[PDB]
Structures are given as C-alpha cells and as structure tokens.
Amino acid sequence: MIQRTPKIQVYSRHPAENGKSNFLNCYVSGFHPSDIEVDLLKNGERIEKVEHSDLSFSKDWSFYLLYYTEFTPTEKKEYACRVNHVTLSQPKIVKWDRD
C-alpha cells in the first residue's frame, strides 16, 4: 500500500480563449489512495457546480485531480480548495493566493 498526501495547488487561470473567464483550480496531485474529497470554497462555502474534476493517475498509485471551475473572484471572498484525504488528518484548505 502506498498513501501519499496530495499536493494541493490552488490557482486561477484564464483560458486564453476567454480572458474574462477565470477558473479557480485546485490541482491535487500525487495522491494515493485516489479516495479524496476536493472542494473549492469561497469563504467556507463549497462551490457546488465545479465544472471540471479531471482525475488522472500516472503510476497506479499517483493520482492527480484538477478540480476547477469558472469563477468570478471577488476581493470580498477568499477562495480555497479543501481537500480531504486519508493522509490529511484534517481537511487541508489551501487558499487561492490571487495576487
């Protein structure tokens, strides 16, 4: 068995086709097992309709999830990614550092 804590990166990307589109991304990488809970948050609020949850694996025991959705960030909110994984005794919340 192997378990690997996800690396969690939260970042925004504008698809080059539409600069006004902005995706909040939670890239959860390298984890195993694949069981995982990933949410994008705005303040504590789960962003419900995350358009993309792209899971892949490299090696059988390394999973990668790009969990991203269009958003329109306000300065008035914090955006984060919350990951639960067995390796994470507490939900890991990684804030988007937009600047």
Image (cartoon, rainbow, N blue to C red):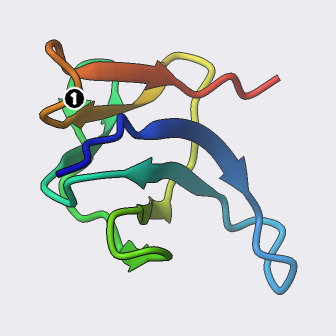
* Nearer-the-camera pick, 85 or 70: 85
Label 1 neighbour load within 10 Å: few <14, some 14-19, many 20+ = some
Which quadrant of the rendered structure holds the C terminus? top right
Give the amino acid at mark 1.
Thr
State the residue position of label 1: 87
Number of numbered discs overlaid on the protein picture? 1
Is 12 placed above or below 75 here?
below
Query: Helix, strand, or loop for circle 1?
Result: loop
The residue drawn where x is 77% and y is 64% is 14
Direction bottom: furthest residue: 17
The residue drawn where x is 58% and y is 28% is 96
The residue drawn where x is 36% and y is 34% is 5
The residue drawn where x is 68% and y is 67% is 21
* Nearer-the-camera pick, 59 or 64: 59
From the top left corner, tell me how far across and down residue 41 is, in percent: 32, 33
Is 22 placed above or below 19 here?
above
Is 36 placed above or below 23 here?
above
From the top left corner, tell me how far across and down residue 74 is, in percent: 58, 30
In which quadrant of the rendered view does residue 16 lie? bottom right
Direction front: furthest residue: 1
* Nearer-the-camera pick, 93 or 3: 3
From the top left corner, tell me how far across and down residue 38 is, in percent: 25, 46
In which quadrant of the rendered view does residue 73 lie? top right
From the top left corner, tell me how far across and down residue 51 is, in percent: 35, 74
In the rendered structure, the answer to whether residue 94 lies left or right of residue 87 reads right
In which quadrant of the rendered view does residue 18 lie? bottom right
* Nearer-the-camera pick, 59 or 73: 59
